Image (cartoon, rainbow over all chains, first blue to last red; front, top):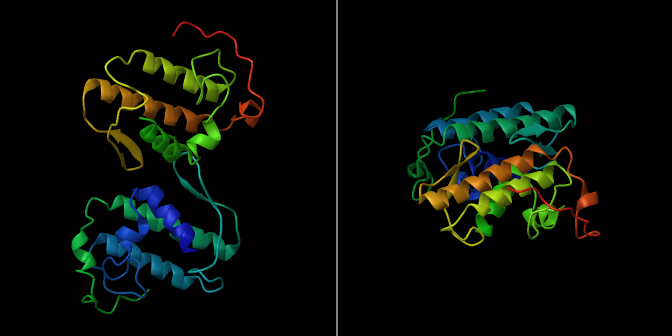
Length: 122
Length: 122
């Protein structure tokens, strides 16, 4: 669940998950999928693609366990679907940190419905 | 200051610096150096010598600035003293993480303190 999502993102990026990626671009906090606007927006994209393929456990709500060992997110050994869920969450936090270079507050908007195009399909 | 130290330990280790090392063994979270009981103990022993050599800086109280960058603690410039102070803390946050395999709550002085022998000359 997002409670674990937030813990991941703060641990990887150092940034506050809600404050930073709350409403960023066309993926990023928000609900649904669009043509990315930058690479951080692109991370969040892959993540929803990732969530989609999971169709057994409620990715957006159901919980799991990970460990912060030796500065790393190692997924616990949950069930087939919960493990990929953990995995998807790890990827995005990893992905987001790697892209802090290009992060730009710009893509939050002022904070109003942006111009989002239909996403490329997963 | 203890504010920054606390933050580093948490960041590297993932534990409350007060719960976990608040009073641990001969040298963690307590006063003076003693002959260390375990590897976690020897972290804080080494850490206190790092402080011994710090004249010109109130290790216990001297605010400095560092950053979390690509999952690493990068110390802000500041003066040599403060630089050194920041180093000591990093190295202790790190040494601590490294030696979680043998953290022994047996030595959690707070449950029955520990008889401590005399320390070596730093």
